[PDB]
Image: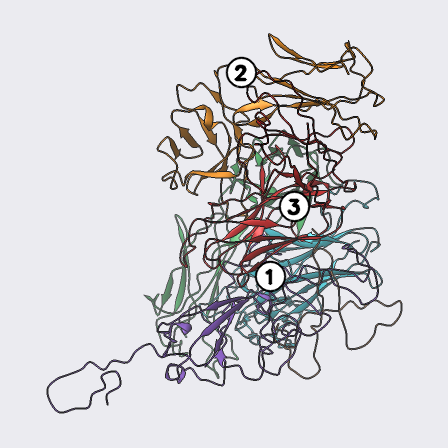
Chain colours: A purple, B brown, C cyan, D red, E green, F orange
Amino acid sequence: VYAWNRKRISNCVADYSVLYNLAPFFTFKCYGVSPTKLNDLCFTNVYADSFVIRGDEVRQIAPGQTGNIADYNYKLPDDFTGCVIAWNSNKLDSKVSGNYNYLYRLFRKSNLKPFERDISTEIYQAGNKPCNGVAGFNCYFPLRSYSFRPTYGVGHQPYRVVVLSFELLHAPATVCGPKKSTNLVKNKCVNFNFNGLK
Amino acid sequence: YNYLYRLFRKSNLKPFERDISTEIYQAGNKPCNGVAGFNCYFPLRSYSFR
Amino acid sequence: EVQLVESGGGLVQPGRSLRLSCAASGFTFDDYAIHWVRQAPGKGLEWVSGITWNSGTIGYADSVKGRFTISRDNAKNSLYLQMNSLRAEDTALYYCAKHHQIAVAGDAEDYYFDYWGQGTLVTVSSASTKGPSVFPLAPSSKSTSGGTAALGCLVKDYFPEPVTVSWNSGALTSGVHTFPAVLQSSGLYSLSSVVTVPSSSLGTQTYICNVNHKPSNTKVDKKVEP
Amino acid sequence: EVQLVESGGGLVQPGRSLRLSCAASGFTFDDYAIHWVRQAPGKGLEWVSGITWNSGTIGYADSVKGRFTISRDNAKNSLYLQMNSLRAEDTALYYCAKHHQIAVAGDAEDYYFDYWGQGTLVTVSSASTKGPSVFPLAPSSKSTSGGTAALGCLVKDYFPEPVTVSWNSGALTSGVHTFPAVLQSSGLYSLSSVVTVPSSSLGTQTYICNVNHKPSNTKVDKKVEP
Amino acid sequence: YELTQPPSVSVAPGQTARITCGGNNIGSKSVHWYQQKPGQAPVLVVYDDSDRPSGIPERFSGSNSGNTATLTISRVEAGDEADYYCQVWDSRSDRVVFGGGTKLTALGQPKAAPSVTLFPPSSEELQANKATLVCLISDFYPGAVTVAWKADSSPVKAGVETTTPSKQSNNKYAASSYLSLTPEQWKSHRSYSCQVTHEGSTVEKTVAPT
Amino acid sequence: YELTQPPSVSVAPGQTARITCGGNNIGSKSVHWYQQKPGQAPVLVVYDDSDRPSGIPERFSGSNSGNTATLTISRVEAGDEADYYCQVWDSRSDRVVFGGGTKLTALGQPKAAPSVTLFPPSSEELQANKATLVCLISDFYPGAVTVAWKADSSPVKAGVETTTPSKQSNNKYAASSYLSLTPEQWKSHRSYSCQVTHEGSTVEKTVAPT
């Protein structure tokens, strides 16, 4: 959740309908948009941010909602336009091969800047003490992780969470709607829409 | 998870008293009903020993 | 001597929690290890967890880690076992077994049970508890031998089966054939018993069939008449 | 083509931490997995960790869990590996290997390396870094054949061995026998090189032996004379 | 760990039985055994393959050699039929590994003719609609019995039945039967009866035709 | 997982070599191989036992059958002596299991006489106390060479020496030697020299007696 990938999409035709084809028990909460009107507006670049946050912290992944995971790992301003999907994958992620495969951070010297990654290496500092790169009192690794055993409750299973950002800058006609066809019939006087002409 | 570890409670423990409990934690205003949901989770957060 | 009475158990919905207890009596609850072991009906036993003479966890199984938490209370002489997020594969008779050795300081880890108990049927399903229905089976007048006539009860319509039948006060350990229950294709069960019931000349039992059902607590004290 | 330059590495005390980097150049750092693999001197290799094309950890070894944390940065095209609580069994050449396949969405997990690098000697001990001592080995006047005379350097008194010798600017790839170092029962090492060194008639090399040592950073530009 | 036990081992009450529990490298770790009567609580038998608890006779014995622990019981009787389990520690996983117990059954026991006991509907149920006619049978050694119902002097099996399997009780099998598919006016005519058909001879018993 | 490889496999440059990697149930998972020249970076060889990368000749081949993956190299030459490793995935543990590589050495190569090169102490060191007299030798195929020092025309071995083992360099072994136990007044008399004793004939070379 502290080191999240950011994929940059290019000119294409995004079909926002396969999002609800995966395994059940998945959220589709949007902010500022709607899935019914998703394929109506035009966006230049869409960014996908994948992270493995789980538990009762998906509700606080929203503009103006702090918490314990969206406080020093991911911050969203009050302008987010996208839909978050948090389907649960408790079949290929939770395994006994390794419990520290995923990571998780904690409090820092300051709050994270919205939409900024905080890949660090340095050890945490309590404010007044010599660390010297050792694991002692008041100097410990803030990357406190958790285990993933295939016996936990519903509130601790691996949740694959990915958010989508919708930007709108001075750009040409980029991704906007999958398509729209109506099985053209040629027998009478009827309306037509040939890619703009109405 | 052979060893355990507790967390914050509704009140501070009385000195030299054991607090063996089963009751799941309560956030203050919500129905728990013995399930693992939002604001109702097991306060016995343990750690690993590798 | 040793009386490992076990309390706590019944019908609970999948995903809930419950507390099991095992009050020890007869020995000192400071020098003997007591463990928890389940036993599925006709499908062998299975070890759950255990605690040594002092407050110490000895481990769990490969399917109960993170969900079950065992605790020991030496002051009240009772062992407790917490169960969280119960599923359909947790229906078994959880027993309360002790240990034979005194668990001296310098030895090798080798635990084997010596005293066993009775266990509590912890059923986990989506069904609901139903009230029993005791009926005074008529001791018909078919008299060929001395004790050929017999009377009993007809307990039925109950999903859980912690059934215990009494006659006068928890006594009369003579011949009483308590037939096992059977799922009548609807989840319910049926109980019945048969006694000797000799020639009735106002010199026989009190004609009482006390049936105790914990998930459906109700004291039935109905009599039986020819 | 592919230039997997690796930075970060040297002598550190047991129990400290350091940051390793591997700047990618030649390919796209968005569709190829890059892993970390160490190689003890003359004792085989050993896989440390790895990350797929996206930000994803593929696991660690059975001896680096909890201490090592790998991170991927697609913006700067560099893979980082954090090492905490280094011990005596962590002295090896950590390499930066790529992956051949493009890691399509629906496939089977099968990672095999295709492009390798050079690695950084990460030595972990209690000793301290020592300054090298370059000496202008005299090209004696023993002249029998054409290029029988040879001159070189006599680098010594250095505990770490990230030694790289240059002559003019990082060039003259001709015959230069750089003999390996040797621990002279004190932790230090000794370096030396031999060149062709033809008949000296003011038409030969500049007689310069540039020695770069990262844990003991010092630019030695001393000349060699007969 | 993982212990492997025979699913069922039968032997005549003239010789000894052979119950084994083998693993991968179980040659030094202690091997404990248990005996559980059907319905009752598990009792302790010879443990550590070198001693027995207080109360167990000399007939019970054990021996382990390399990868096989043999619980050699001598002079098996009828009262010795129970579910025998073997225990191991396996300190490598910090568990208590059990295994599928063996159902020791003394083969060659005398037969036992089951006695059927008819119980008509009670008195305080005709005012309501219960329809819980019960047909009971006594104990019997040869199991696998089929209870055939003769409702209204005719074979009626389409109704809701139970047909419970024979259970264990003092080394004697027993079962029950329930079939009252009637509209609760069971006192129609022709003596609604019950039948029990065992292997060989069958027992018959009816009730009053009212 | 755990792969087992032969510690060393030698073969004359007339036939093929047999390098195998066996496990427990490695019959379906892909088997990848690697070749690492001594000192250089590991290069890629035939992978998946069914194809080779771009650049590898047809001489390299592989095959897996049940529990054995054979890296069949054809027409082994002198330039093929390297450390060969085999790779496996073992998705059961989410790791990358390597193994002890095999040192393929082409047996039956021609001999190579080593040339000794004496380097006296430099000019800008007599003012200080360095005492780093170096005696170097050229490349040679037959390794296991003992450098005998002749200090002051007499066998002196009690001093601090190095005696580095022969390393690999373009398929030719080479080493060095350091012994300057002198009080730094090495220009005493009798031509402090150096000797190299190979298997068979030995090479001698001294310096100026000053």
User: Badge 3: how crowded within 10 Å, few (<14), some, or many (20+)?
Assistant: few
Residue F176 shown left or right of residue F4 in the figure: right
Q: Position of residue A32 (x, y in %)?
A: 49, 86
* Quadrant in the picture for residue C173: bottom right
| Residue marked by disc 1 | C196
Whether label 3 touches label 1, CB < 8 Å:
no
Residue B41 at what x, y percent from top left?
66, 72
Task: Tell me if label 3 and label 2 are in contact, CB under 8 Å.
Answer: no
Label 1: few (<14), some or many (≥20) within 10 Å?
A: some
Rendering coords of residue A141 (x, y %): 72, 60
Nearer to us: label 3 or label 1:
3
Please tell me which residue lies in front, E122 or B31. Answer: B31
Outermost residue on the top side: it is F200
Which element is circle 3 on? Answer: loop
- Depth check, mark 1 against mark 2: the one in front is 2
Please give the residue where the numbered disc 3 appears in the rendered image. Answer: D63
Task: Label 1, secondary structure: give it.
Answer: loop
For residue A78, above or below residue F157: below
Are the residues flagged by discs 1 and 2 from a single subunit?
no
Asked whether the viewer can see residue C161, the reply is no
Question: On the picture, is E22 further left or further right than D129?
Answer: left
- Amino acid carrying label 1: it is Thr
Quarter of the C terminus of chain F within the rendering: top right
**C-alpha gap between disc 3 and disc 1:** 72 Å
Q: Which mark is on residue F112? A: 2
Please report, as a chain letter, where disc 1 is located. Answer: C
Q: What's the distance in space between the residues labelled 3 and 2, CA to CA?
A: 44 Å
